[PDB]
Image (spheres, coloured by chain):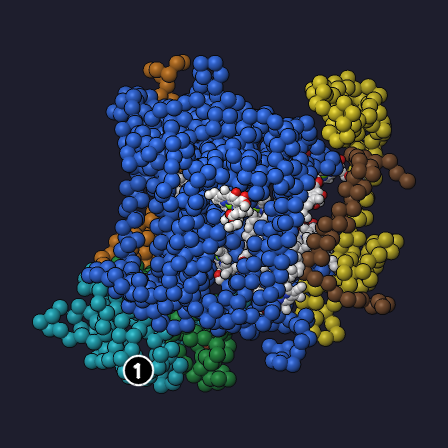
Amino acid sequence: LVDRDPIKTSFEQWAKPGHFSRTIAKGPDTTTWIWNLHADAHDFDSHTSDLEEISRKVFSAHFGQLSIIFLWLSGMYFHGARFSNYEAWLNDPTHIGPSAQVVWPIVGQEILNGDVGGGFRGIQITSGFFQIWRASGITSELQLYCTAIGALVFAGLMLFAGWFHYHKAAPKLAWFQDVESMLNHHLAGLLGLGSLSWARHQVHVSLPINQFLNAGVDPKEIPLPHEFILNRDLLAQLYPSFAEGATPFFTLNWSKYADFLTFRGGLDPLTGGLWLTDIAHHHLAIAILFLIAGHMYRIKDILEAHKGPFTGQGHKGLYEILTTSWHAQLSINLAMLGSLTIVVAQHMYSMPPYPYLATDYATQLSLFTHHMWIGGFLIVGAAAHAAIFMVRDYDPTTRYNDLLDRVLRHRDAIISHLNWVCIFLGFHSFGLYIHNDTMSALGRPQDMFSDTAIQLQPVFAQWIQNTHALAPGTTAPGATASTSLTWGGGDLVAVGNKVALLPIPLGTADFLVHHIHAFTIHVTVLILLKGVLFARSSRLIPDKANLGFRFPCDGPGRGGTCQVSAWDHVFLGLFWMYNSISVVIFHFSWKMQSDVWGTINDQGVVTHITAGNFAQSSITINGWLRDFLWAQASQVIQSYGSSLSAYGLFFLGAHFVWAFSLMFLFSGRGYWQELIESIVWAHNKLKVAPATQPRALSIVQGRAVGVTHYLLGGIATTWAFFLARIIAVG
Amino acid sequence: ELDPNTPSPIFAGSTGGLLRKAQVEEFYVITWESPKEQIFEMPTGGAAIMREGPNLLKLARKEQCLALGTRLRSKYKIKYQFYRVFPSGEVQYLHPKDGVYPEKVNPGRQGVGLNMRSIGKNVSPIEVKFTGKQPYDL
Amino acid sequence: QAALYTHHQYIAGFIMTGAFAHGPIFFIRDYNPEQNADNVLARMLEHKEAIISHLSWASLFLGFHTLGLYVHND
Amino acid sequence: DIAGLTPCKESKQFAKREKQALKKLQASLKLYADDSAPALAIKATMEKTKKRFDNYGKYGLLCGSDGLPHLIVSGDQRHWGEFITPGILFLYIAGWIGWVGRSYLIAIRDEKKPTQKEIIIDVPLASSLLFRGFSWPVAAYRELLNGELVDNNF
Amino acid sequence: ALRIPRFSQGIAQDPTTRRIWFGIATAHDFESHDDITEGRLYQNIFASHFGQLAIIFLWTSGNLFHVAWQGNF
Amino acid sequence: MRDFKTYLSVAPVLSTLWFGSLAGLLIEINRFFPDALTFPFF
Amino acid sequence: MSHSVKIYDTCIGCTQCVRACPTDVLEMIPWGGCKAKQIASAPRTEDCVGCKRCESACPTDFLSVRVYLWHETTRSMGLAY
Ligand code: CLA
Ligand code: CLA
Ligand code: CLA
Ligand code: CLA
Ligand code: CLA
Ligand SMILES: CC1=C(C/C=C(\C)CCC[C@H](C)CCC[C@@H](C)CCCC(C)C)C(=O)c2ccccc2C1=O
Ligand code: SF4
Ligand code: SF4
């Protein structure tokens, strides 16, 4: 390509058919290249055979995410502001049931807008702003309206840094191809200087402006816009102005104190969102580390070190090419970023970190399943992109004889095991349930697997739960309750509208879901593991790195020779994970409502959204639609003519879109060709078709329009199924 | 084996190649030339070196041992050579035979390309009912 | 009366298919273009691109138009 | 008149629908807007579905049991424009979608390399072959069947 | 490496398992598989579905036989 | 600046300024007549 | 047949056209006049598996081959092991 250059046009390329592999989009017309162009639009086997740029693009086309997450948030802060309900909800929590969005009464619309709290028509929320927002050491609607434009500021600017890259004549190699410092910085002072900084604006301002909110008032009968400077006088109620101490150290006297923190654990009676008196200390006690920690270092050295006998000789030298990969140092990350998201999903529901959550049921489970699909949707990826490594990234083979060349050495092996693992599971991990049916429908309970028939006896208790809620008696200092109230030992009194967390008991019907997870988590990974491992060569095809990591299927021979590849192992690996997460969700809420969520009154006689129906009745896998799907969902199929209605009214579409995927999943290809011409014929008679040769779907595009649909179908189905059984009773 | 140790194509371990069905039936093996000590890619997932001897690696099945070409001719050399070992001898002299480099002319050998009638209007389906007296066994 | 209209609706449907499926085997194993031609079983082949189209036009119409009326209704 | 019942001039079942259902729209003794200037069930949403009283127009409109109105359209008693009036309309509008389909198309296949001019658009919508549709008096109803797209080109 | 399945031949000495499945689903495809003639075939569907009518009466018999001694009538 | 026998181009999805809008002006007829199901004429 | 999938064309020239396919195709057998004069459709095919890598490149202008062989050894599917 010209047009023409090198050097010697500014005149930009708008006009002249094509670009992207060289007997390119050819003069001669076609359609396939219009899904080409969008797909693989980002890729790197083309653009140039030379690293250089690519990192100079990804550090820019990156940017436009932050900026975006930044245009987003703004319409959420704005939204969570003038489309109010926040002002109204906060003087009045336990009571309200929040909104931010509202229609405009065009056509049918309005049904969707149904009285939500501080006196107005709207559609609800299961996205816990209104609750980060508890923070506001200040309060005010127009104020969020500054935090809002403060958002659009970071954006335009944190979006003109993206002009101020690639398009501007760019940095180069050394800049990233000296890695030497990167984490040094990152973790030290941002990971640090945020958490740190967050400390300073987490007791300064917030703690006090909810220390005396957890009582009454109406805001501006509290927390001015400046009030919190030098005036270290209201900081007087929430500890000393250090009195006689000077910059910690010890020649200090406490005859009666010990700074803010004074460590909690449990839950505010009046706002059980976990205590804040702590929340500063923990973030402070973070940062320090990061503050000390981001001070390594300059790199091989540490990895060029510990080897052994069978261990990893190539451990030593574990990648020069880890300054020369991406597709590698992205895949690693996704496993972590991803696997480090759904660890949120627990510490959240068994330890709320915001005021008013749990009581708020629906506004932190939405969460625990949204955060849950990322700690999964980012993991199969975290494999895909390793397959993208394993196939291609490096120039030649300069990488040699090491940890990997090792793992591969065995490979019909690491995956030889893992397999049997799964059929051991599955048999012990699902037909287990099927016993029950076949023998409870035969009907002889003597011999089921009930929490009571097969020998276990009115106790689960003695394991580690019961040595967690009881541990404030070790090296442990203490502080009433535990760490997470859901643990075996002691305490009850949690909240005065509805409930929050309490013990959460186990045994079987907790024993075996917990095991289906195993088998589910395991056969997921089998297919990804073997998939990324056998990326490039095999004894079904060895001539098998020769195009890319996709390729439809090699060809009718060898018997099958179809699925193979690794786009496709990252195609049938999604297919499982949709279950992996989709059944983990199914788990939590049936627990968390069967027990936990429920409610106090006199003598606090607890009354769960369901008197533990779980008991003897999830163990039957029909009980999973006797007690679940057919029981709850009665709220989705009753939901017409209401306010939420948009869920029942989705629940048919998307419970349709899924049942459209199979068409894309289950079908041939020269088929819709053979068909597309009958069409093309009738077209030509009137004189109406040929130009831009209309073509069927690109074997693997077809699979691309399976899967993606099967998910946005099979998923939102419950996104509806859910929001419709926590809004309204529960 | 060892008391007779005759090697050439360096490797160390691997759960890849050759297993039970290469004794009890057929064998298949590739041989080659090379300049100075160079590290290669490998069928079966692994990777090692060269120098010489016969440079004679043995391989499970013959689709496997020509892939030394589909990359092992993007790494210099005229000469690479795979035969067929049995559990006893010959017939099937695999890369032996006559000339070499599938795209030259000495003889014609087999192939043909036609059937009875050529690609032309076989809208004509299957003809006679299969019956032992009219030239359809080819 | 209601598990007997259907074992006669399944089947029946289940047939039809196989009916349509041994009449696309005639065209390959048997059948004989030189022995059937200008002849009304041909012409049926010959004028075929139309046949699937003025069939597909029925469906796509009978498609979105039933599906307008049923989501709209929902 | 026909299979269902009579229109609006009387339709008991239909009446009950007007009333319960909507007016329970009510259902919120108050819900505070004594004077307040937002929450608009209050004004219309009802009244816009409601002041739709014993009038909706008058439309005839058959209304079965439960009094949801059914559409006959067999060109009789009253009901004619529940298909034809909005039927020819569907025809006319489409067909002037594709009359121009068969137009910002039959204007290209010529000159010099014309092999995807169509992924960009030469005259947007065609904005030239545009009105050819309203500028269809008769048109394809003759020139389609005689000449141009002539059996020749068939 | 032996010889088996008594009608086809390509199928007959295929060393895998296909050997099996594909055996039990080519059975009924008389027209053109080793053992066939337009004379064979026809009759080889004729005394086939004389093997029919035949299986329809062992059905009906027992239909009228789990009825006559119990199963209210 | 645009006379007779076709004109200047336009992008991939100006359909997104054709679905959104034009069609958009039609809600604009579906509130002017906030309702249908038959229609009076002019 | 026993491997019978027709990739034939008319040029049977094989330069920047087609080579790919494990062993099976030792051609260049010049028939007395067909331009770049190398012809036909195969050599001795009782050796390797069932690709259609066979065309994918260099014309067959008609069909292109695939599996059709039925009578199917094992050395004819990777897996006789
Ligand atoms: C006003 C400015 C402007 C202009 C005229 C250009 C022009 C160009 N840029 Mg570019 N760029 C810009 C701003 C601009 N850029 C900014 C602000 C950034 C950083 C944010 C970049 C980052 C960038 C990179 C990495 C590259 C270019 C390249 C190019 C060249 C190819 C452009 C192209 O066709 O992409 C078409 C794409 C667009 C027009 C849209 C850009 C996508 C982002 C910024 C917004 C869209 C996201 C949006 C939310 C869509 C998703 C939601 C959807 C549902 C609506 C071209 C000369 C490329 C090059 O050098 O040639 C290989 C190179 O790849 N640019
Ligand atoms: C940190 C990571 C992130 C990044 C930066 C990338 C980057 C990349 N990935 Mg990738 N990937 C990721 C996470 C990431 N991935 C994850 C988590 C997965 C697992 C699902 C994958 C699975 C994956 C595959 C299989 C492939 C890539 C490929 C690529 C490359 C192609 C990108 C492209 O052209 O856009 C592609 C995006 C589109 C074409 C847009 C279509 C999006 C559709 C499906 C919409 C999604 C549904 C949604 C609900 C619809 C919107 C709403 C609608 C209803 C209105 C690029 C380098 C491709 C490659 O060939 O590598 C070179 C290869 O295809 N990725
Ligand atoms: C009333 C019947 C009628 C008759 C006389 C025939 C006769 C024939 N059919 Mg045929 N067919 C029919 C109805 C009939 N068909 C119908 C209704 C359909 C589909 C609706 C088909 C679909 C069909 C196909 C696809 C083929 C034939 C073929 C044939 C020929 C070989 C038979 C065969 O392959 O079976 C051998 C089968 C077996 C020995 C058993 C395997 C069958 C499996 C799929 C079991 C089916 C489901 C089963 C009930 C579920 C398991 C039970 C469960 C309770 C455990 C033979 C000419 C073949 C042929 O020669 O065409 C070129 C083949 O192509 N037929
Ligand atoms: C419920 C399912 C789903 C849907 C919607 C369809 C739809 C269709 N199938 Mg199909 N199919 C399915 C599942 C589905 N299938 C499954 C599971 C299988 C077996 C595995 C098949 C096997 C099959 C075969 C063999 C064939 C079809 C054909 C068809 C088409 C027939 C024409 C028609 O019915 O009206 C048209 C379509 C509809 C009524 C569906 C809605 C499509 C429109 C309304 C999309 C909506 C636009 C929307 C607002 C924009 C959103 C897109 C985006 C911008 C966000 C139609 C497109 C046939 C065909 O090709 O006809 C020519 C025929 O080939 N199907
Ligand atoms: C300009 C348009 C045009 C015209 C005149 C036609 C005409 C026809 N199509 Mg068709 N089609 C089109 C575009 C068009 N199509 C497009 C874009 C697609 C998507 C691939 C199809 C997919 C399609 C299928 C599957 C079938 C037909 C069939 C038909 C025939 C039956 C009519 C019918 O019931 O389908 C209704 C029409 C559609 C479903 C097409 C939707 C696209 C329309 C809305 C195009 C609108 C104009 C477009 C924006 C062009 C830009 C304008 C430009 C001047 C600037 C008829 C000859 C059927 C047939 O073969 O039987 C004879 C068959 O069922 N079409
Ligand atoms: C149904 C199906 C098809 C047929 C599906 C097709 C042809 C979908 C493509 C339809 C396109 C998206 C229609 C695009 C037309 C419009 C974009 C043009 C008009 C512009 C708008 C204004 C309407 C395949 O091609 C296929 C391929 C491989 C495996 C499975 C399948 C499969 O299941
Ligand atoms: S290249 Fe393809 S003759 Fe030509 S189509 Fe036949 S093998 Fe050679
Ligand atoms: S197409 Fe057939 S003959 Fe050719 S290489 Fe592939 S398998 Fe062998």
Q: Residue C10: where, in percent of width, then height?
A: 50, 35
Query: Does A345 appear above or below B62?
Result: above
Which of D90/A470 is in front?
A470
The percent coordinates of residue A613 (x first, y second) are 42, 23
Shown colour of chain D: yellow
Tell me, what hue is chain G? green
- Horizontally, is G32 left or right of D37 in the view? left
Q: Secondary structure at mark 1?
A: loop
Q: Where, by quadrant of the figure, is residue F40 drawn?
A: top right
Describe residue A720's horizontal placement relative to residue E9 as left or right. right
Q: Residue at x 38, y 65 (%)?
A: A298
* Rendered image quadrant of residue A266: top left
Tell me the quarter of the image containing the C terminus of chain D. bottom right
Where is residue A269? Give x, y as percent: 48, 25
Quadrant the N terminus of chain D occupies: top right
Apparent side of residue A220 relative to residue A700 in the rendered image (left or right): right
Q: Which chain's colour is brown? A: F
**Residue closest to the eye, A158 or D121:** A158
Mark 1 crowdedness (10 Å alpha carbons): few <14, some 14-19, many ≥20: few
User: CB at mark 1 closer than 8 A to ligand 8?
Assistant: no
User: Residue lying furthest right in this view?
Assistant: F42
- The chain displayed orange equals E
In the foreground, A549 or A277: A277
Q: Residue at x 52, y 22 (%)?
A: A497
Chain letter, colour blue in render: A
Tell me the kind of residue under disc 1.
Lys
Instruction: Find disc 1 in the rendering and name its residue.
Output: B79
Residue at 44% of width from left, 82% of height from top?
G38
Identify whether A352 is placed above or below B12: above
Most extreme residue toward the left is B3
Residue B114 versus residue A574: which sits nearer the camera?
Answer: A574
